[PDB]
Image: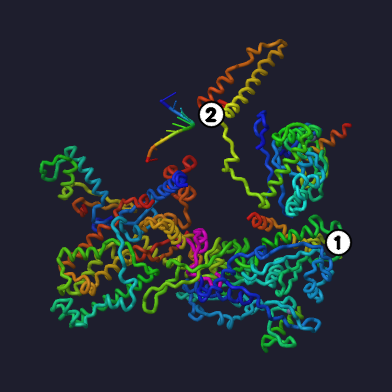
Amino acid sequence: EGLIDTAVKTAETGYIQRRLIKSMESVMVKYDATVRNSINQVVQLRYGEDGLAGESVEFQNLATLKPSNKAFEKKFRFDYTNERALRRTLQEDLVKDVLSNAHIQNELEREFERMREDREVLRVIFPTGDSKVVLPCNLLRMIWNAQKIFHINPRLPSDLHPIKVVEGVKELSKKLVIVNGDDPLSRQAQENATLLFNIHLRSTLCSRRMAEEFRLSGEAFDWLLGEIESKFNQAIAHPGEMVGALAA
Amino acid sequence: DDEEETYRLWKIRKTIMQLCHDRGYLVTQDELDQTLEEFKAQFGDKPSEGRPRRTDLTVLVAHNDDPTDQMFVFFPEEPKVGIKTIKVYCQRMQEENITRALIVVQQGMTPSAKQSLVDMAPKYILEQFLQQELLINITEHELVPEHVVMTKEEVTELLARYKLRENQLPRIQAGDPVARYFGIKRGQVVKIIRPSETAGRYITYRLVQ
Amino acid sequence: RSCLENSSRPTSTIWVSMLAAIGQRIVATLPYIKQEVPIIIVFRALGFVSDRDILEHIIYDFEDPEMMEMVKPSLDEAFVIQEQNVALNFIGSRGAKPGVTKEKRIKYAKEVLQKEMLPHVGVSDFCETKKAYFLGYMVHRLLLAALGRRELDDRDHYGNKRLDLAGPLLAFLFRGMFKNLLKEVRIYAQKFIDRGKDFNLELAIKTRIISDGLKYSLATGNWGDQKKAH
Amino acid sequence: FLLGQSARDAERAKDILCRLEHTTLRKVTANTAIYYDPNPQSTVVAEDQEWVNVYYEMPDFDVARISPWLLRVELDRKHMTDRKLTMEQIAEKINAGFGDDLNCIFNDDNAEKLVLRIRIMNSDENKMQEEEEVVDKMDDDVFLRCIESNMLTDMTLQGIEQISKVYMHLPQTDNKKKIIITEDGEFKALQEWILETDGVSLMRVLSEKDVDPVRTTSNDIVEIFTVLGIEAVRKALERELYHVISFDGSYVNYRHLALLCDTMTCRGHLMAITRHGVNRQDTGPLMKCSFEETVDVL
Amino acid sequence: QANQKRITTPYMTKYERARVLGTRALQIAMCAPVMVELEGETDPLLIAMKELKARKIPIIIRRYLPDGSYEDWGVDELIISD
Amino acid sequence: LETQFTCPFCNHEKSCDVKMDRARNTGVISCTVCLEEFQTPITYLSEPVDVYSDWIDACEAANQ
Amino acid sequence: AGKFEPVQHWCRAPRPDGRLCERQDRLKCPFHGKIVPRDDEGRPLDPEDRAREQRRQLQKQERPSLTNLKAQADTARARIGRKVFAKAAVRRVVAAMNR
RNA sequence: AUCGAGAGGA
Ligand SMILES: [Zn+2]
Ligand SMILES: [Zn+2]
């Protein structure tokens, strides 16, 4: 029976392979980053739905999807009020700034509110709570690389001000562009094409995890932002990619 | 038996009010969420006794943007609607000066009535629904993503942004269940918002054909 | 697939089939007859006229009413034909050329029933009892299958199969070649008897037919007439 | 998928199962017989005079209209009670299907045998139209055999005609369990009854009273396209291809499946990966001829 | 299309790199002048790769858009990813 | 089977057609060239060629 | 998934004889309609349901030329025949028979 | 040299 199946299955599968190629052979990423057929009809406005090449993405976990509300708050909401925990996590001039500067405290609070909103968006996208997702830049491995390149001692307080984390992640998000243009259609399509990656970026690279868990220094964080930018741009699909023949 | 017909009539009414609200006609929250016992209280519990008659079920609604833009919903009593009944509704629409109506039919519609819906279409737009296809609102089903009918201005902005002709958009048939639900005609565009497991969200656009 | 014990002709296949008030009707696909015949008409053409006498060939124990109920629709269907001559006419109306006289249609039907239907049971006259019993056995086997009392046959079961070796394979060729040789001997000699004079048979026999037919088929492996190689 | 308590109580799930699965009279009938029973007052079947007389010793129907041919059907208790079906409903379905032209009477459920008695009711004028009493087809016993053959197989007692079988089970796998977000914000899986069917009739099933109309779905994509439209079949086709590809644990990057499903659906209708789809696009003739139908295309 | 707002990606594609290197190598083999100093390297394709890394290749890439417009980009304007 | 026949009287080929009047259990065969017609009782088993055979037999019976 | 035959109750409306009914119908009685609880003289045990049932009993108590060729087309046996011999009906039957 | 057939390899 195994010899029969080995001899008989092959014609049907090879015919399926042929028909798929002949159905998709001219489907290509254009220089406008839309995916179009030979009659120039739009099949996808961005390849995949995200503009990325398939070879440059890898499995990652969305850290905010599964936690309970208490564990989410405990892990992600920066506590600027426990002076001794700050003193154990941040150097003295940072603790003095964070304890007193109400503007910085408001920035940290609305950082957390943006994570809370992102969590509710994820809960709609992944209603079965499977956190496993495929995304371009492996953030945890890049953080582990920064930890080793810059000899980060996990047991000492960091010089990295949490406001530099908030601002740096806001500025990085503006450089990861899949849909170009200032008009509201471009702006909305850009927000959509990068929503899940930006949720992952904000939740991984939040001020509290950078203080308590990753303990990166300022120079290591400055390196991490450039690494993420460079690796994201290398993941974008190249015009002329014959993505139909690849899919077939 | 009457407990079945009254439930059917209630469900159909609820779906029609949801449809009217989604088309943008002014529908109150109270009638949008009316419960079965409130339907029994307002219209009756024995339609075989004629309580309600399906003539009692008729709906008239006006658009949120223009109180003179109005639509009927008619529930013919006969199971298989013929041209006589269409002519009666055409007359009522002419005297009330109402250009849109939905005709909800129990079993079907005659070929002559079907053609009569085509042959008056520029001045009076009549649409057919079976009652069976109104017993569930298909737009609540998890496979159906959010459909938003675009304005002509928004279509001009879309085509200008992506520098494309209408014939280069992907299509939707005018007979598509959701196109029929929204009542969209040839040459309109529907924006579709769907979640995506790789971007997070994706919008696509379909030209009605 | 009936074949006479000596291969004077190729096999002829008879099908008796049960069709998919409505009831299960049994019909025969006989050779050289254009249309399926109700089996009870075939039995009447073989000369068994009463329904009881027919069922005695098909249902060996009458105290079995489940089989009786299953033959009953076929006794109903054929009841309009009740005499052997009408049945032989009915069969002969089909297959025979439409214009021929009644005697020729009857004779055609008798010829099919003797020589073409079930030749392994016999090709002689007075074989009709043997043929009625075997055709009755065929219907009985079909009834046992329809009632689920006997299992359907397996085409893979090697008891149901035969291996044609070199001998039978060469005999198949040599029959056709000897027939073509006799044909050509008739064709040669007739244009001498048409010319009123005796012929030398040593010139009539074109020995190339056998010598090159067997040689060609063994050379190429096309097992048949060289003219029909595809 | 079921709503409400019918998702927890197995008896309510079984009630919906009976509401879906097609049951004809044959599925609940043990045997049928046709009798010459010319006087219901002295029925030739002995075992049932005690109830038959109770129907005729009252005025609602007239023995002068009764045909002497009786159709007698015996039902069996297990198949009736597995369906919560009653002979009052069976008779109601008979009279709904044939009107007043056909008379039916039935026994008490106290009996060890469930029986109903059917005969043609001849409410004609007694015209001397005596040429075979009908212009061509049949006598009443052959006609009643035809009525039996029809009633056994083309009379519906419950269910949807296309739904040949229904199964119910608890899903062991979380992909079919209901997932909820708790008040504490955790995901939780709920083990609830689902029904799986052989045969499809999505539009009828969605409209059943306790069926969850949000989650219930077919695997037939043409049914999805007909009931729910082009974007629904775009999502369902992705689900079905994903299920086939992932069944052995293999993984293919989503964008390949997405691009195939978009190619199959961008024209607004289900385009087959076959000459009947690919070679009906606006692609030029040289592209078409490289696939199939080479000479006819040109 | 106006040149003041080019909208195509500023990165050179893998296909552009491939064809630019091939075309430039064939030019060098046909005795086109070389825009870089050579450490005695003689292979036209190695020379082309030196000129690519130097940003000295005298070639314009004309990127056609789906609407039939185009953008002209110099090889020295593009970011080289390899 | 063939459903058009040569006329026994006028020898024209495919000139006779059969009308199966099932409701009256009677079959009529008519020649379009000479309009000779014949009627025979038919059964549900009966077919055009049985009507033609009945006509040829009636003709040969009249030659006696 | 369980099954039982709880039919200890009886239809207890009066017969035309004035004797009470004794038929063990489950839910509908051919002579009496939908079954309801009734007293020792057959009156419903519901002041309102006995009124709706009395109104239903009142509704039940409240409810030349040559031989036209259509007059043979209305007989009961032709009405049944047009169903049972319908081409679609006979096909759906034989489709179920082949299965 | 072509056409056809058969036997083999992965
Ligand atoms: Zn003639
Ligand atoms: Zn009673």
Q: Say if residue B53 shows up in the picture.
A: yes
Q: Say if residue A187 shows up in the picture.
A: no
Q: Which mark is residue B76?
A: none
Q: Amino acid at mark 2?
A: Asn
Q: Which quadrant holds residue D109?
A: bottom right
Q: Chain of mark 1?
A: G
Answer yes or no: do the residues labelled 1 and 2 have beta carbons within 8 Å?
A: no
Q: Is label 1 in a helix, a strand or a loop?
A: loop
- What residue range appears in magenta? D207-231
Tell me where residue A97 appears, x and y as whole percent.
16, 80
The residue closer to the viewer here, D221 or C46, is C46
Q: Amino acid at mark 1?
A: Leu
Report the residue marked by disc 1: G66
Q: Which quadrant holds residue F62?
A: top right
Please tell me whether residue A208 belongs to the stretch shown in magenta: no
Q: Which mark is residue C222?
A: 2
